[PDB]
Image 1: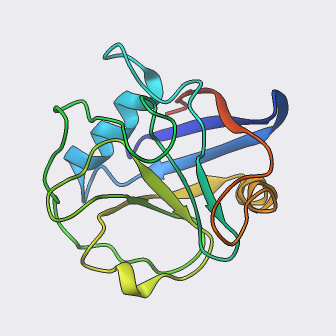
Image 2: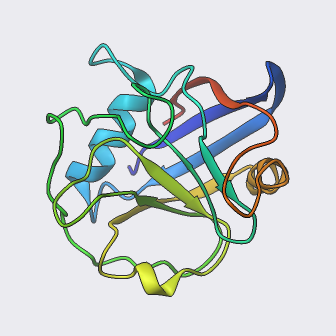
Image 3: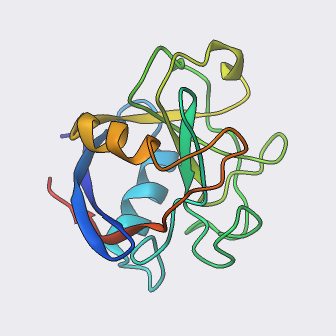
Length: 164
């Protein structure tokens, strides 16, 4: 009943693999719906073709800025920003999917995939999903990151959508 979405990753145009994600629509329905709809592109905009602009090995992979491709843009299906829905779920380890933001109630489209336990983000960032398949592809992506987050190659979401 919780949606599964997938991302097909490419590194400088060449296919790397697929990562799928379970979205916790049961606990964070509004946040889960925003990610799901941007993954299918059904509202007319979304993640397809966008890049992961910030990857820091041992911490996280960040993407979701489909309008400025660098951390300064993006928007939700509800408008520019939307509220923190709740903080029920915690950043308990690698594989966690969480919303990036710029302050309270400033969720747009940017998100990060944790590759480590990041307990200090609890109560500041809304957790809404986790990697279901392809954690090994997220580990492969990390090796293209760096300490300041700049990627040595262009990491893009070549395709995305809903599996269930």
